[PDB]
Amino acid sequence: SAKVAFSAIRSTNHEPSEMSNRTMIIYFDQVLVNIGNNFDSERSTFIAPRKGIYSFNFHVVKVYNRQTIQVSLMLNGWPVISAFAGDQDVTREAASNGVLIQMEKGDRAYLKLERGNLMGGWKYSTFSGFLVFPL
Amino acid sequence: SAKVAFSAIRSTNHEPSEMSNRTMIIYFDQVLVNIGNNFDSERSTFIAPRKGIYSFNFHVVKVYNRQTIQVSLMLNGWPVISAFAGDQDVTREAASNGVLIQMEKGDRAYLKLERGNLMGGWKYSTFSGFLVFPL
Amino acid sequence: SAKVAFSAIRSTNHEPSEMSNRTMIIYFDQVLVNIGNNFDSERSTFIAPRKGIYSFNFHVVKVYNRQTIQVSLMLNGWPVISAFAGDQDVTREAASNGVLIQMEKGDRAYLKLERGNLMGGWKYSTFSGFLVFPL
Amino acid sequence: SAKVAFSAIRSTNHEPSEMSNRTMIIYFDQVLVNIGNNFDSERSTFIAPRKGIYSFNFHVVKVYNRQTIQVSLMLNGWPVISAFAGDQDVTREAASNGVLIQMEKGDRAYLKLERGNLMGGWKYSTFSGFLVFPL
Amino acid sequence: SAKVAFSAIRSTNHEPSEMSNRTMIIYFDQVLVNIGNNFDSERSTFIAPRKGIYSFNFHVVKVYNRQTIQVSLMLNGWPVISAFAGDQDVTREAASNGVLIQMEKGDRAYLKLERGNLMGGWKYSTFSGFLVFPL
Amino acid sequence: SAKVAFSAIRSTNHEPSEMSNRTMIIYFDQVLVNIGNNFDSERSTFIAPRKGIYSFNFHVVKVYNRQTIQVSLMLNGWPVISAFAGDQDVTREAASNGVLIQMEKGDRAYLKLERGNLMGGWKYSTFSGFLVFPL
């Protein structure tokens, strides 16, 4: 099975859970796609089923909360790429980035909030990825 | 044929047509890619040729027009994801987002302007997508 | 071999080289992925190994430097898509865009800074791409 | 035959055809010169009969129509050079530019309206070119 | 002798002569080029020495004089192409156009002011042409 | 070799270099044509390879910058022809002119900004020329 893909979104204004405050992980409640069921909705983490090249993209949308944020794509607890978002009232803005990375089986991919907070929710945020090809 | 991909751009400053004002659909005049010819340039809509997981990305670039906008990726008249863009003069900014979604044959994908307008044109805007794998 | 993919990042605050000032090319020092070794790290250019549809994405992250920038994806010295980024101190912002394009063998893909400069470095910038399918 | 040259003008106030609105191509009804008959009056396109260096010049004259325009010289669907024209009532003004380019046989040259419209006609507009020398 | 070319400019602020008012011909006092001596400086007219395709270009620069002008390239007393120039104080503007035309021996080419006047002079105006190839 | 031709354009919004401020020379970064390699891109100067009649054309496109400009075609540090452009916001306008001149070997041709500045860039500007015939 060379078919692996997942897609998740934040569909609500809901505030960060007390757990979110501790782990600093960005959680996505609604899963649009999860072929291979390799994405754990509960922990919002992608566990690679096999060795290959994976694509990842994320858009974290925040609102005016007196904070500037930094979102990082994590690989086994280590940051790979980062995105930023300023603070202003006129509109929502998104911390967006994406990358291709090689992963081995059991490698964990997820989003962590390196700075600031997501008070006011992070509705419309998106996190998706898929296996480009195995190795 | 598991090869399906399209890519379109807004190559001009030209203003929204009277039709654009009615349908609120964002139109792309120039098509860089359209394998399978599943992208209708006239209506700027992607019709899925088969059941599978599709990837979508869009960047809608606007200019200072006294308006803040919201672009949404539509699936059969229903919003899937959204992007936003504030209003200021110093630079152009883009409403960008992307997602993986499952589609069946005859499902329609396109961009709709949920709020604000694109007076001053939306040149440099991009909309692309491809079949990741069928199902 | 239908497996082709590359991924590069700017991992440092380091200033533009004197060469960067001349060629206006955006350079990425660290390569996360380079299957097929079709990405030349030295010139930060992707040379297509065969005819097919390729995907490209880039995020150029700049800091407050009194300048507004424009990054363009180049194809054989011709711009395909562009991205912009304003100037303010509260946060970093990114010039981001992406597209699917058809390339033939020996076609060159790379990023050029059409306007402004990247004084203060362009750390956290990303540039990636892969062969979706050959033709 | 190293003798190749064409010259065309817009001799009337007539409005853009419904076709013009779709293709965004600027059409010239009257042909003053067409040695080698390499200029297609119907599509207002120059098809190079051989490899060489060609000269091109164009003046697109518009009237007060509430629009600002941008005319581009196209080479196989790609812009080479561009010209602009503001909007005011006191006089007609022209979007003018010219260039020398290398073309191979079967290369297509024509003018496209990148932005705005030519309501009120584009009378007195001119488009001409010739083979400087072959290669 | 297939070498034929001329180039003339208006090098002074000087007003239109009483003769200019009658004939409506635009005169150029200084001749930069006149190979074949086929350009008559006195009457500012090009007399074709042989049958061939000739290129012509002109830029008539006027100043704020309460008038809008129209310059036409004349061929044996008949207009071929025209150019226009509005009226405003902030800058000089030019009535510019150019064309390739077939001429026979003894055919006369010159510029005529179809409307308005050139009070305030037409300094920096240019008129040039050359034999592209004979027939 | 009677084949000599060059063509250059300003392809970016980029501001005048500190060097531009000193020398007042208008620089063109992108070269479309340079047969005989007689055009020096670095100094944006054409050095005649032989004695003959050369054609020159230029369009310098500026934006609203609170300044009115004057561009002159220079021959060995001496002005030959000039063009002007007013200041207004509704559109870009171009300082355009052209001429045929006799040059000897080692004669230098280039564009100089006689007045005003090109803040806001001079994108879409064009400068081209070719040997009509030798002498």
Image: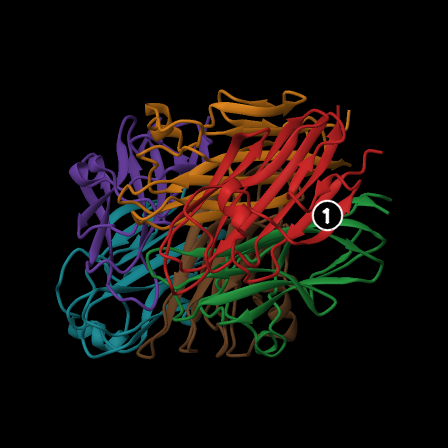
Chain colours: A red, B green, C orange, D brown, E cyan, F purple
Residue drawn at (36%, 24%) of the image = C19
Which is more toward the observer, C87 or E76?
C87
Which is more toward the observer, E120 or C26?
C26
Quadrant of the drawing holding the N terminus of chain E = top left
Position of residue E33 relative to residue E21, above or below, is above
Give the residue type at disc 1. Answer: Phe
Position of residue D134 relative to residue A33, above or below, is above
Position of residue C56 relative to residue D113, above or below, is above
Q: Chain of mark 1?
A: B
Residue F5 percent across, percent down from the top left:
43, 36
Element assignment for label 1: strand
Is D121 left, or right, of F16 in this rendering? Answer: right
Q: How many marks?
A: 1
Residue drawn at (20%, 79%) of the image = E66
Which is more toward the observer, E125 or D61?
D61
Which is more toward the observer, C30 or A69?
A69
Question: Label 1: which residue?
Answer: B130
Residue D10 percent across, percent down from the top left:
52, 69
Q: Is residue C103 visible?
A: no
Position of residue E59 relative to residue A54, above or below, is below
Q: Residues within 10 Å of mark 1 (few under 14, many from 20)?
A: many
Residue C123 percent across, percent down from the top left:
41, 32
In the picture as drawn, the residue positioned furthest to the front comes out as A18
Rendered image quadrant of residue F130:
top left
Residue drawn at (40%, 27%) of the image = C12
Rendered image quadrant of residue A35:
top right
Q: Is residue A93 visible?
A: yes
Residue A64 percent across, percent down from the top left:
40, 60
